[PDB]
Length: 61
Length: 61
Image (tube, rainbow over all chains, first blue to last red; front, side):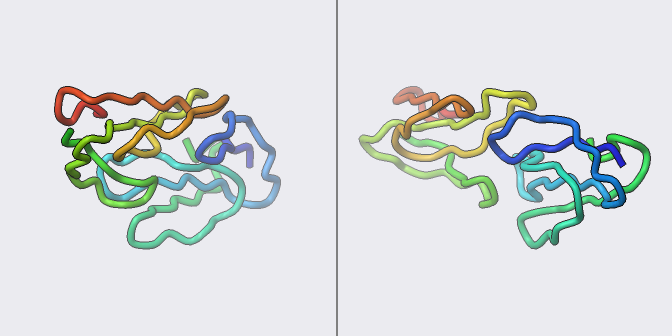
């Protein structure tokens, strides 16, 4: 899948993740904002929601 | 000054910073979002803008 990718400070770029999923990592507590996007599907926890998707392209918007 | 305060994952709380300023730390590159708020006035750089203020209360919104 094609996915957006950035850390909390890096420029957002497009990345071909191939056969991995895309993820979108957001904070759960207000103010709710996306902290990171990339390839794979890392674990969320009490403060962080991690959405993982494989379709469409750029699904981790 | 009274200031908002949170890290990238912590719950936002109100904090009496006393005689320090408030800061608001934002990313410069899209998507532009606030990564952190607190007491003091840490340095920004190429990826991070840091606004520092002393008035009004909660100025680092």
